Image: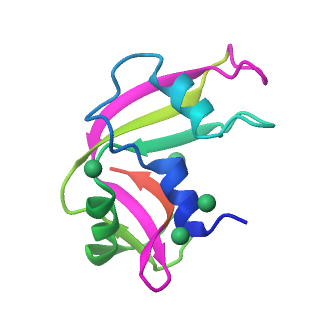
């Protein structure tokens, strides 16, 4: 079974680009990160910063998570992100995503020792 930290990395880290290159970024990344296996994952955010910088958010501003838990943290700085969301033309298989690039603060839930990101809560 994948660890929670490793699942966060696979679903939400893309340090190899500064920003979504094009409208097909999400179609490609959703497929390559194995987020379209049996179902199209409906919504997923990728963060274009170093893993270290994203991990560091777990020692930044403590904020409530949407679900009311208290282990969420909001990045002090904005980060380059791409939101991927399924379009109306999307029907498994042949998932289809809209790519939206933005520079926003991220909010992650953190857990463990080391205390690292395990869920992507939101961007602001
Ligand atoms: Cl793994
Ligand atoms: Cl791990
Ligand atoms: Cl997400
Ligand atoms: Cl990097």
Q: Is residue 103 magenta?
A: yes
From this view, report whether residue 100 is shown above or below residue 43. Answer: above
Please state the extent of the stretch shown in magenta in the rendering. Answer: 89-117
Identify the residue at horizontal 29%, vertical 31% (top origin): 19
Quadrant position of residue 114: bottom left
Location of residue 21 in the rendering, given as x and y in whole percent from the top left corner: 33, 21
Ligand 1 is found in which quarter of the picture?
A: bottom right
- Viewed as shown, does residue 45 lie left or right of 81? right
Identify the residue at horizontal 66%, vertical 17% (top origin): 88
Q: How is the image coloured?
A: rainbow
Q: Is residue 110 magenta?
A: yes
Location of residue 25 in the rendering, given as x and y in whole percent from the top left corner: 45, 24
From this view, report whether residue 80 is shown above or below residue 91. Answer: below
Location of residue 6 in the rendering, given as x and y in whole percent from the top left corner: 55, 62
Identify the residue at horizontal 58%, vertical 59% (top origin): 7
From this view, report whether residue 95 is shown above or below residue 56. Answer: above
């Amino acid at each position: 079974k994948e660890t929670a930290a490793a699942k966060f990395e696979r679903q939400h880290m893309d340090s190899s680009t500064s920003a979504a290159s094009s409208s097909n970024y999400c179609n490609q990344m959703m497929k390559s990160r194995n987020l379209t296996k049996d179902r199209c994952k409906p919504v997923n955010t990728f963060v274009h910063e170093s893993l270290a910088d994203v991990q560091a958010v777990c020692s930044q501003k403590n904020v409530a998570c949407k679900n009311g838990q208290t282990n969420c943290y909001q990045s002090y700085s904005t980060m380059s992100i791409t939101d991927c969301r399924e379009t109306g033309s999307s029907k498994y298989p042949n998932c289809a995503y809209k790519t939206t690039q933005a520079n926003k603060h991220i909010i992650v839930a953190c857990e463990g020792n080391p205390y690292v990101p395990v869920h992507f809560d939101a961007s602001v």
